[PDB]
Amino acid sequence: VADRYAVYWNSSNPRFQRGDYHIDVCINDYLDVFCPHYEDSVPEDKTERYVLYMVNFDGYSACDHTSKGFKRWECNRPHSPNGPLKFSEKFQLFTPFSLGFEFRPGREYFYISSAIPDNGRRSCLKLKVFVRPTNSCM
Amino acid sequence: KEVVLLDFAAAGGELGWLTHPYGKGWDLMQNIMNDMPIYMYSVCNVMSGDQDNWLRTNWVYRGEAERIFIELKFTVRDCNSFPGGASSCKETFNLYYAESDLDYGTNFQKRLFTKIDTIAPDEITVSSDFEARHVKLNVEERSVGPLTRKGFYLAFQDIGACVALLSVRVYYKKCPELLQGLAHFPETIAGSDAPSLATVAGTCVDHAVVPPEEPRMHCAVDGEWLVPIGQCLCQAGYEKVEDACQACSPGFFKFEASESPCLECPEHTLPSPEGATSCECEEGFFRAPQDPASMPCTRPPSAPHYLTAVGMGAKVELRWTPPQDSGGREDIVYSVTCEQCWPSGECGPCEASVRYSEPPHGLTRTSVTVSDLEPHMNYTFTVEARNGVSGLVTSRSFRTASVEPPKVRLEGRSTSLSVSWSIPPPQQSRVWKYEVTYRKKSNSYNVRRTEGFSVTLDDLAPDTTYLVQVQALTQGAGSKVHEFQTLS
């Protein structure tokens, strides 16, 4: 893309229906997660809600955050005002804040989600982020 | 009480503050803490040397705020915990502010801002804090005043530190609406100057009043009411119940504005309605214009229980006693009047020639001497008893009283004295016994008694003067003192 990567986190997105959704980024690039957004004319039953987790492979591969992940974001406002609720992740080297999230070139990172109303925790929506090595990034 | 003007943490990341330079310094980060979604402005350019990053808050309408308090919550990272870590790493950041009449919007000029203070962390975040998920959140508060212009900005300058701003909270202090001393005090703003004591007049709550000092409170800069002056009182018919004034209960009363409760109705009184200043009197009883409403209803007294009118000599002595019934009063006075009657038959008021040993009215004594009386005249004296409530009734309570000795001679003597006497036959029935007293011409005399009209004093000294008196006793009248001498 460019410097910011928009990711629409819903089961209707073809990108997620292929099951291998991944993005190649460089340090200081951004990840913009757009939660599922529905107009007020929806019974909130077909409305999708998710809890997003940052996990490792085995968690990523098994769609399981237990003991292998941090709770990252919560898509719990299917009716937010200014369009879809958005969460952003900056792939920075060093965090300004105690215990912020740091990223390293040449490494892979993983996000999975579990439906709030719960569908079965089977084949979760997932995203792999590949932070390119310094050699690749310009 | 605190009025909030700015609260970052509560805005849910919708504030969108201005950063400078454009898209280089502070960034809006989002994370989860305590299972809650939170936002924060953070910056960590610890490797890039000279840093000068500004985060300016949105324009804050001042309103009535004079001194604002700024509460910052933040974390700062250990400069030692950076693999590289140039000597350009700082562990502080700067707090600025700027007053303004209007919102400059996207305009940002640093040199408009005045530095408030350097912000330093009590707790530094170390590298070990990282694998332990341990957040050391510092809390720092500053204050600036007096604010004078329509509004103001707050600005945060990073000079090369590893910081994240979790919370920004600006507020001013407000002396709370107050109910005290039966008065009401409006919510007022804490002045800006430290030695500020704003005098706030109070308003008497309903049915309350200032009797004779008017209620006043003094608002300090920290929002405390300091020194109370004056008060409102629950006036007549009202008392203090909790924090307000309430009408006196049925069967109670209150006559003045005091800090006392309602007194229950005294004796001989009629049950009172709510908010009574005094209980009405029971039938046949009264109260004086000086009696407290705690005093039972009273009434005029009865007559002086006893009255004696004795004509000892030429004067007449009037001796009486307090009434059997005082009517429940202690302010009893007596007054004496007189009638003349010639036993002629005609009668009339007493002459102006009659005197009293004491002004015949307003008597507190129970006796008076009457002098200068015409002989043989039948005088009738009336002594009246009156108390405080007498002037409130027409009736009178009084008692009346109207005002011959033995003629004695010597029938012979020796040495003894032979004595005889007499009184008109009509009087002879009245006398029970005659009492003969004989003393020697200072504290020792002899007295005998007989129903007859003659006695012989025996065992006397020769050529001696004796004082002899013969009194007529009844169930009385005594003669004059005679001097009889014995033989030689």
Image (tube, grey):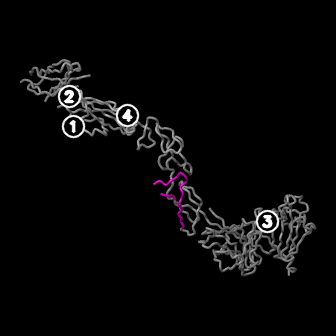
- In 3D space, how far apart are the residues under numbered discs 3 and 4 (Cα atoms)? 95 Å
Q: Report if residue A79 is visible in the image.
A: yes
Farthest residue toward the left? Answer: B488
Q: Amino acid at mark 1?
A: Ser
Q: Report if residue B139 is visible in the image.
A: no
Q: Which residue is mark 1?
A: B353
- Whether residues under marks 1 and 2 lie with C-beta atoms below 8 angstroms apart, the answer is no
Over which residues does the magenta segment extend? B196-215
Q: Are marks 2 and 3 on the same chain?
A: no
Quarter holding the N terminus of chain B is: bottom right
Chain under disc 1? B
- Asked whether B136 or B203 is in front, the reply is B203
- Asked whether B57 or B333 is in front, the reply is B333
- Whether residues under marks 3 and 1 lie with C-beta atoms below 8 angstroms apart, the answer is no
Q: Is residue B446 above or below residue A113?
A: above
Rendered image quadrant of residue B301: top left
Q: Which residue is mark 2?
A: B376
Chain under disc 3? A
Tell me where residue B474 appears, x and y as whole percent: 24, 22
Q: Amino acid at mark 2?
A: His
Left or right, residue B343 beside residue B411: right
Tell me where residue B472 appears, x and y as whole percent: 21, 23
- In 3D space, how far apart are the residues under numbered discs 4 and 2 (Cα atoms)? 33 Å
- Asked whether B260 or B226 is in front, the reply is B260
Tell me where residue B396 appears, x and y as whole percent: 35, 34
